[PDB]
Amino acid sequence: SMNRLGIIYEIQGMKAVVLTSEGEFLIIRRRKDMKVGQQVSFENEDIYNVRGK
């Protein structure tokens, strides 16, 4: 659980755009917790960018 914090900036179906505390836009898996506008705690494991592949 490598937790990263980001604000749900936008949603792409099952993907979510998070504007992190770093000010970076990352594409993550959208969970049911993802509401547009809120800062969510996700894992790096949720990140579609930093998947590991």
Image (cartoon, rainbow, N blue to C red):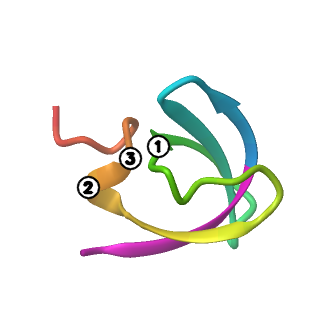
Residue drawn at x 26%, y 55% is 45
Identified by mark 3, the residue type is Ile
Q: Residues within 10 Å of mark 3 (few under 14, many from 20)?
A: many
Q: Is residue 48 above or below residue 31?
A: above
Q: CA distance from mark 3 to mark 2?
A: 5 Å
Residue drawn at x 47%, y 43% is 28
* Number of numbered callouts drawn: 3
Is residue 15 shown in magenta? no
**Mark 1 vs 3: CB contact within 8 A:** yes
Instruction: Tell me the SS state at disc 2.
Output: helix
Residue 28: give its label: 1
Q: Residue 12 or 53: which is nearer the viewer?
A: 12
- Classify residue 40 as left or right of residue 21: left
Q: Residues within 10 Å of mark 2 (few under 14, many from 20)?
A: some
Q: Residue 53 occupies which quadrant of the picture? A: top left
- Classify residue 19 as left or right of residue 53: right
Identified by mark 1, the residue type is Ile
**Mark 3 vs 2: CB contact within 8 A:** yes
Q: Position of residue 43 (x, y in %)?
A: 35, 65
- Classify residue 26 as left or right of residue 25: left
Is residue 6 shown in magenta? yes
Q: Position of residue 50 (x, y in %)?
A: 33, 44
Identified by mark 2, the residue type is Glu
Q: CA distance from mark 1 to mark 3?
A: 4 Å
Residue drawn at x 64%, y 64% is 6
The rendered magenta stretch, by its main secondary structure, is classed as strand
Give the magenta range: 1-8
The disc, 2 or 1, on the residue closer to the chain's N-terminal end is 1
Q: Which residue is mark 3?
A: 47
Q: Is residue 24 above or below residue 48?
A: below
Residue 45: give its label: 2
